[PDB]
Image (tube, rainbow, N blue to C red):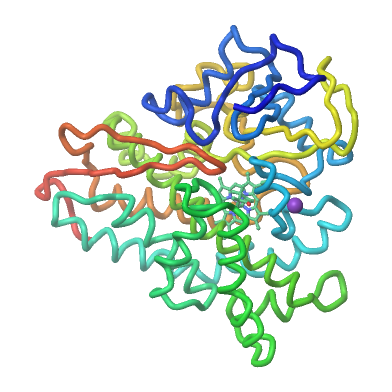
Length: 404
Ligand code: MNR
Ligand SMILES: CC1(C)[C@@H]2CC[C@@]1(C)C(=O)C2
Ligand SMILES: [K+]
């Protein structure tokens, strides 16, 4: 715990630990939902991880992400040392300076690139699933959730697959550190990995994402090696620790709900809609902003330098935004959420993300329509900047499957 600030009252003090929530046993989304009970106010202050504010309602979360004049992304992570050390592009920048870098990033992970990767995304998903199909079991996180998105990213970035263990270890320390590395150390290690590669590719320009970024232009002018490094690092974290985790949350749910599997099996055209609803119910990101100065936000005096966590995860879980929020309804009329962010920093990889999600759902249910959680298994989650699933052992009767 950290000493309570002067401007911070006492009634709004909710000691929530984003890296180890109290009710984590009931599921991470459930763990964060406690901040939305009637007994909890919209905005509270926690003395965990150094102390910071936490907007618990979609209304304030959205509003803050729109007002970059008061809530700067210069220091988006908690603890403060992580946020101060955090210098990824375009995320650590505020408009207007931020805007120019998003276009370059779009060139390597935007829809146009997703279109090119279409065949390979499809091919890998089918190959991985068909290999598991006759086994009647798997460790989903390790056998599919990780290799599917990560191998696609490494392909696009032109990096050898043998480097995945090292890179995945580093990305995970920046989102869910095990204590062996500070965010700054993990970040510098990722940059150390990228530096020589970016230099190599600025000399012999290739087709990969790192080459395109490294030799790119920012609103008409050349990108520096430092700027390319800072952008490439972010792309690595996005490709290695986002969809990877979400897929496990989604499959855990399907493994636990036969009725929902049946729905998508009977009406595959609903998969895209199902994806969106799962993105809301199993939202998993939570980063924030920093006050550029003294500001009275919703009757709560915010001082300059103060960090405020704006959980993208909480918006769509707000009973005020969606009726019966913890319930998964593929026919939900208005699936409200900020799973991919809000404001000028809206996720640039959401198109690649949705394609990977939709393809996984369609191709998995096509070959393994029926599956369940391994008997006696208790699924354990993990919380942090990006929440995840520790392990997801699945089982099924091979006789109920079908090879395409
Ligand atoms: C490899 C590419 C990426 C993939 C895949 C990907 C997949 C996902 C994903 C999967 C389910 C979720 C959820 C996700 C969530 C986010 N994502 Mn996404 N993301 N994502 C980026 C690359 C990627 N994301 C980049 C780049 C930005 C920064 C944009 C900017 O700062 O202007 C971004 C930004 C964001 C933000 C904004 C954070 C902020 O405002 O500080 C959220 C939230
Ligand atoms: C919060 C995020 C998911 C977004 C893309 C990767 C991430 C960890 C960042 O640093 C920006
Ligand atoms: K910073």
